[PDB]
Amino acid sequence: MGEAEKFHYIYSCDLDINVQLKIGSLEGKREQKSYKAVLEDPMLKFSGLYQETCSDLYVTCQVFAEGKPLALPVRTSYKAFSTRWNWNEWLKLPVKYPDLPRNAQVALTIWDVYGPGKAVPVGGTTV
Amino acid sequence: ALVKEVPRNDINIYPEYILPGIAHLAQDDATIVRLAYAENIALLAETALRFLELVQLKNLNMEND
Image (cartoon, rainbow over all chains, first blue to last red; front, side, top):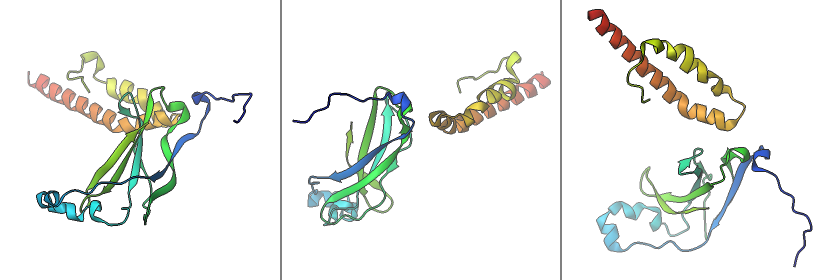
């Protein structure tokens, strides 16, 4: 059991630095579609779902407040994944500490390749 | 963007009040302000341009009245 007799805090309006969130690793299995699904849309074969290794996914993080995006989405640099999706990348968000409203949320969407030039979401989370 | 008719007293509202009134925002110290400026500078200009086109059409019609 740790200890801390004093709580040190700062008002979000007083921290004049950008808010950074590091998208770490995505742990878990992404389910493959049936062959009938590949028959319905042949482009599915060329999708990242059909790469045997962990596809090189990236997460675009955009801050929303009251449903309106505060800034443009920031994307993780391309990284080649072998056995695990581990980005370990500190993302510099386009939102400053004083500019975040109380109801501010970060939406992170993981995207994979879906044929030539088309990205399809693998899945999303909002915190 | 909702202004569809320009009152006679505001024909020069854009060059002297709208555009000069927000011009200081394009250089604001707060990045959120400059961001709001960059996000809207394109819209503000397009809105002023719509106003100028309406004033010109109205002037052409008033000259033909």
